[PDB]
Amino acid sequence: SVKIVTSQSEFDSIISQNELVIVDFFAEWCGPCKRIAPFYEECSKTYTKMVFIKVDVDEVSEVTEKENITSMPTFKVYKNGSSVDTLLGANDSALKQLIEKYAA
């Protein structure tokens, strides 16, 4: 069950209240989020060791600046409340290896 956080501190909170956290920084006017969600769902039930959340850039622009988000869609995994890895382009297979690497 991918988690959607609508707060800036709540976003950062999720990052710090867990060892490893994976977030899909995305936009609502994009299609990949919808196309990447189906695979993301599978990843969420096996990779449950890793916490999955969703943070939009429009609701909390401050979040974008906090993580220096330049490209999109971007998938980043956070360790000890810090950025640990980045994945460009919402790809089921690409995230598969990225999510599997730290989560699997």
Image (cartoon, rainbow, N blue to C red):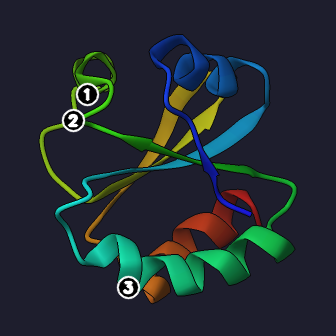
Label 1 belongs to which residue?
Answer: 64
Q: Amino acid at mark 3?
A: Arg
Label 3 crowding class (10 Å Cα cut-off): few <14, some 14-19, many 20+? few
Residue 56 lies, in percent from the top left, at 35, 42
Q: How many marks?
A: 3
Indicate whether 62 appears above or below 92. above
* Alpha-carbon span between mark 1 and mark 3: 22 Å
Label 2 belongs to which residue?
Answer: 69
Q: Amino acid at mark 2?
A: Ile
Image quarter for residue 80?
top right
Image quarter for residue 62?
top left
Residue 61 lies, in percent from the top left, at 23, 23
Earlier-in-chain disc, 1 versus 3: 3
Please identify the quadrant where the N terminus is shown. Answer: bottom right
Residue 103 lies, in percent from the top left, at 74, 60
* Numbered disc 1: secondary structure: helix
Would you say the residues marked 1 and 2 are in contact, meaning their CB atoms lie under 8 Å apart? yes
Left or right: 100, with 46 as reference point: left
Residue at the far top in the pictured view:
9
* Alpha-carbon span between mark 3 and mark 2: 21 Å
Q: Nearer the viewer, residue 85 or 40?
A: 40
Earlier-in-chain disc, 1 versus 2: 1
Q: Nearer the viewer, residue 1 or 101?
A: 1
Image quarter for residue 17?
top right
Label 3 belongs to which residue?
Answer: 35
Q: Nearer the viewer, mark 3 or mark 2?
A: 3
Would you say the residues marked 1 and 3 are in contact, meaning their CB atoms lie under 8 Å apart? no
Residue at the far left in the pictured view:
70
Earlier-in-chain disc, 3 versus 2: 3
Q: Amino acid at mark 1?
A: Thr
* Alpha-carbon span between mark 1 and mark 2: 5 Å
